[PDB]
Image: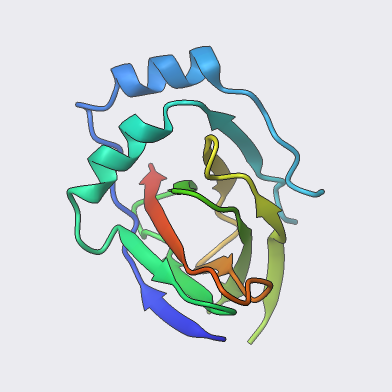
Length: 34
Length: 124
């Protein structure tokens, strides 16, 4: 019931910029705590 | 102190998965009752963390801790997310130099493994 993975933070691609426009257009906030 | 994170969702789940699928290490397979921690160090050239994730058929527990460099801070508490119906995403502001612990908790699932599609970012 446990396993650790190491990953470097990538950088937001400029290609996926229209992907951020549809996001903000559809971004629907959710609670961090349920 | 420590800044609260923002967390949201968006419906383009089939689109998101197809982009992520193309990468080998951006897709985890969390097993029955398994908990996969993803250690994401702060980028020395960065000030914020972002995350995107999703799964295919079932939900999965998700939360985020922060390890100082064993002192921990609960950034996002681990609750189950319906990341199989919409793409789950969020951001948080670096409090200092440390390692973000992205918890993908499946401990509650006795029979189902979860195929996680995720990707992490940073901004200067």
